[PDB]
Amino acid sequence: GPETLCGAELVDALQFVCGDRGFYFNKPTGYGSSSRRAPQTGIVDECCFRSCDLRRLEMYCAPLKPAKSA
């Protein structure tokens, strides 16, 4: 929700969600082929205003064997 996870904080969030286990960023991107048009919400914005976290983000951290609609 409305709390700015920016720079270090967004890395920290993404790292605990996937990072240390796995990763593939959605910068403001969509996986495989979709452009900087915030398709999969858009990491930068979803983090640095919307709190990218454990139940808000994993869908664009690494959706692997752990894959979730949050």
Image (spheres, rainbow, N blue to C red):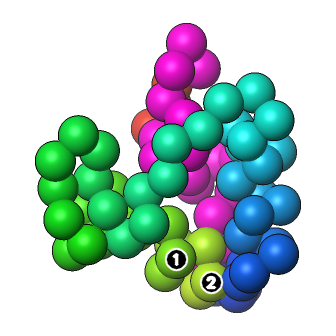
Q: Report the residue marked by disc 2.
A: 48
Relative height, residue 36 to residue 3 (above, below):
above
Closer to the camera, 2 or 42?
42
Disc 1 + disc 2, Cβ < 8 Å: yes
Residue at 64% in and 47% down: 55
Q: Is residue 33 left or right of residue 31?
A: left
The quarter of the displayed image where residue 10 is located: bottom right
Give the structural element (helix, strand or loop) at label 1. helix
In the image: residue 8, left or right of residue 44: right
The residue nearer to you, when weighing 55 against 39, is: 39
Q: Is residue 49 above or below residue 16?
A: below
CA–CA distance between discs 1 and 2? 6 Å
Q: Can the viewer see residue 63 in this picture?
A: yes
Please provide percent x and percent y for residue 43: 50, 67
- Residue in the picture at 83% in, 61% down: 12
Q: Which residues are magenta?
A: 50-66
* Label 2 packing within 10 angstroms: few (<14), some (14-19), many (20+): some
Nearer to the camera, 31 or 47: 31
Question: For the N terminus, which image quadrant?
Answer: bottom right
Amino acid type at mark 2: Cys
- The relative height of residue 38 versus residue 4 in the rendered view (above or below) is above
Note whether residue 70 is visible: no
Question: Which residue: 19% across, 65% down?
Answer: 35
Neighbor class of circle 1 (other Cα within 10 Å; few <14, some 14-19, many 20+) is many
For label 1, the residue is 44
